[PDB]
Image (cartoon, rainbow, N blue to C red):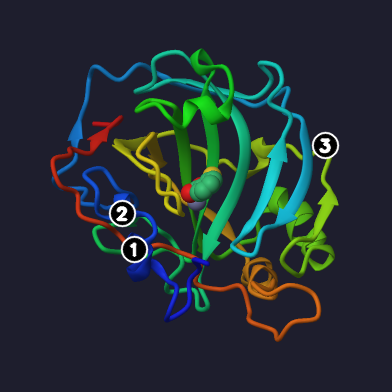
Amino acid sequence: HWGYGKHNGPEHWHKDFPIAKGERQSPVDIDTHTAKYDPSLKPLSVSYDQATSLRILNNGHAFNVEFDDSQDKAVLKGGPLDGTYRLIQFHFHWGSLDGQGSEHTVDKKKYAAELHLVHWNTKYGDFGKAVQQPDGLAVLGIFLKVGSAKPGLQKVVDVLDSIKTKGKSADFTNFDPRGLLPESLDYWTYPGSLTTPPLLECVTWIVLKEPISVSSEQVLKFRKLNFNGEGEPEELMVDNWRPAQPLKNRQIKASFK
Ligand SMILES: O=C(O)c1ccccc1S
Ligand SMILES: [Zn+2]
C-alpha cells in the first residue's frame, strides 16, 4: 500500500486515489506576499481545556494522539469556521534532516516538522459523515523549528520508544494539547484536503504563522520511530511529508494585517 518510499510515495498516490490531482489538494506553498488580510474572519477560538486524550498509535505512517470526541470537550471555532469543530486526533510530519519535514511551506521555506490537529464539524454527527462534506473538517497546522525544547512536547517524545513499530499503541491519557501552541494565533487559511490517502477534499486549513521551537533531541526521537512492523527490517520513520500541491483556483487569506 501507499507510503513515502520511491515506489509508493506521493507521486504514486494518484493511481489509487485519483483526487490526488484534484482541485483543492493540500498542502500548498503559502506565498506571504499574495495572501490577503481578510476582515470577514471572526476571532479564532481554540478551546482545549477539557480535552481528553486516550491513546497514541504508530500507524506505519506517523503516530496519532487520539482524543475522546463523544462530547463537546476540545473544540475549534471562529476564524473562517461556521459552527463548532471537535478535536479527534493530532499527529506530525517530519524530516530526516532539520531542513525539511513540513508539508505547507512559507515562501518555499520548509520547516523541520508540522503538527496537524484534526477536528470535525459537529453538524455532521461523526467524523465519518464529516469526511463526505466539503466543510467537514478543520485542521490547525503548526510549524516546528529546531531550537529551544518545547516542554509540552516531552510527554509525547518520552512515550515513543513504546510504540516504535507499526501497529503499536500506548495509553496516553491526560495529555494537554495546549502545550503545543505558540503564543500567537495569527494564521493563514484556505480550503484544501487531507494530506494522506484518501486525500479527501473536506478541510478548512488554518496554518499558524508563528512556529513552535522544539529541540534537536526531541525531533531526533521522532526519527527513531519505524514505518515497519515488529520483526521486519528497520525502515526509519522519516520524511513522511507530502510536498506542496498546485494552488489552482484558490486564495490564501491572512487573519493579520
Ligand atoms: O491527516 C490526514 O491527512 C489523514 C489522512 C487519512 C486519514 C486520516 C487523516 S487525519
Ligand atoms: Zn497531517
Q: Amino acid at mark 3?
A: Asn
Q: Relative to residue 223, is residue 28 depicted above or below?
A: above
Residue 245: percent from left, percent from top: 26, 57
Numbered mark located on residue 18 in the image? 2
- Determine if residue 174 is in view: yes
Q: Mark 2 and mark 3 in contact (Cβ < 8 Å)?
A: no
Label 2 neighbour load within 10 Å: few <14, some 14-19, many 20+: few
Viewer-side residue, 19 vs 155: 19
Q: CA distance from mark 1 to mark 3?
A: 40 Å
Task: Respond yes or no on whether mark 3 lies under 8 Å from ligand 1.
Answer: no
Q: CA distance from mark 3 to mark 2?
A: 39 Å
Q: Secondary structure at mark 1?
A: helix
Q: Quadrant of the C terminus?
A: top left
Q: Residue furthest bottom?
A: 233
Disc on the earlier residue, 1 or 3: 1
Residue 219: percent from left, percent from top: 62, 68
Q: Amino acid at mark 1?
A: Lys
Tell me the residue at 61%/44% (across/down): 90
Q: Taking 246 as reference, is 111 left or right?
A: right
Residue corresponding to mark 1: 15
The quadrant in which residue 208 appears is top left
Q: Relative to residue 82, is residue 228 depicted above or below?
A: below
Label 1 neighbour load within 10 Å: few <14, some 14-19, many 20+: few
Q: Amino acid at mark 2?
A: Pro
Disc on the earlier residue, 3 or 2: 2
Q: Nearer the viewer, mark 3 or mark 2?
A: 2
Q: CA distance from mark 1 to mark 2?
A: 6 Å
Residue corresponding to mark 3: 174
